[PDB]
Amino acid sequence: VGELRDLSPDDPQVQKAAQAAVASYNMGSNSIYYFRDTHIIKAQSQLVAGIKYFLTMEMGSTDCRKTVDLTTCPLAAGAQQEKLRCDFEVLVVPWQNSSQLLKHNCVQMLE
Amino acid sequence: VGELRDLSPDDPQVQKAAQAAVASYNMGSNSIYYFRDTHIIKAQSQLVAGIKYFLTMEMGSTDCRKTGDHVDLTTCPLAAGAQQEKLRCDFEVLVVPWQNSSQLLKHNCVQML
């Protein structure tokens, strides 16, 4: 992790990263219409390192609703509590306070 | 990009990453209830290097609708008039050369006039 070098909007790798950013946004979007890149204003790149963690973990539903301390929310009880087996992929860089969830894949289990 | 080493479910850094993962899923999830971690089965860690790109860019709505995917935005003309919408977005993209793909990490898009 170093400080970002400024780049040319026309840099071919910048353009590759732009196209990727658009594609993922459109997959994410809540618009029916696809979106397209017009102009690229500011482009910067940083060099980065981090650890990627690969978790397989079981999670249970608590009773608390979303509209925060999860320790104080006790799990649901019996057939009412739904359990999940999830494979997570988390990325931690030393600079960020945050860590990012990259891929997650969850599946329900039987009683 | 290196090999995953298996680690202890109780490793404090593993615990911090589980905590992070849960929070992220909870914001993402389509459940009404928050979820909580019970048991940690398998934990592995991999070392990673790549470049992060920080784009600020303007995007327009095209006429192509949604009803990976097989899209050439080159073939999709921007909208005219009623369907017009312009966005100014700050993206953060991560590219690792070992992997082929790139990942969008943070995006913040804002409508324009």
Image (cartoon, coloured by chain):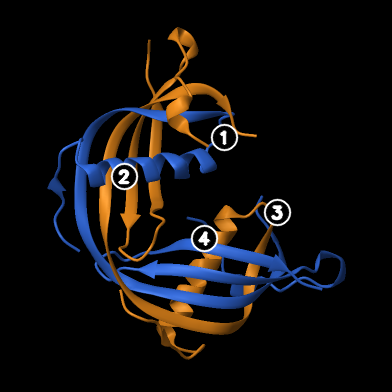
Chain colours: A orange, B blue
The answer as to whether the residues below labels 4 and 3 share one chain is: yes
Give SS at disc 1: loop
Q: What amino acid does circle 1 point to? A: Asn
Depth-wise, is mark 4 or mark 1 nearer the camera?
Answer: 1
Is there one chain holding both mark 1 and mark 2? yes
Sequence order check, earlier mark of 1 and 2: 2
Which of the pair B103/A94 is nearer the observer? Answer: A94
Q: Report how far apart the C-alphas of labels 1 and 2 lie in the structure.
A: 23 Å
Residue at image mark 3: A32
In this rendering, is residue B74 above or below B110?
A: below
Distance Cα–Cα, label 3 vs label 2: 38 Å
Mark 2–mark 4 contact, CB under 8 Å? no
Check if mark 1's residue and mark 2's residue have beta carbons within 8 Å. no
Gap between marks 4 and 1 measured at Cα = 20 Å
- Pointer 4 residue: A24
Residue B88: name its quadrant: bottom right
Near mark 2 (Cα within 10 A), the count class, few <14, some 14-19 or many ≥20, is few
SS of the residue under disc 3:
loop
Which one is in front, A51 or B55? A51
Identify the disc placed on residue B16.
Answer: 2
Q: Please give left or right for residue B49 compared with residue A30 in the image.
A: left
Q: Chain of mark 1?
A: B
The structure residue drawn at horizontal position 46% and vertical position 26%, both measured from the top left corner, is: A72
| Residue under label 1 | B30
Question: From this viewpoint, is residue B113 visible?
Answer: yes
Q: Position of residue A7 (x, y in %)?
A: 45, 89
Pointer 2 chain: B
Image quadrant in which you'd find residue A35: bottom right
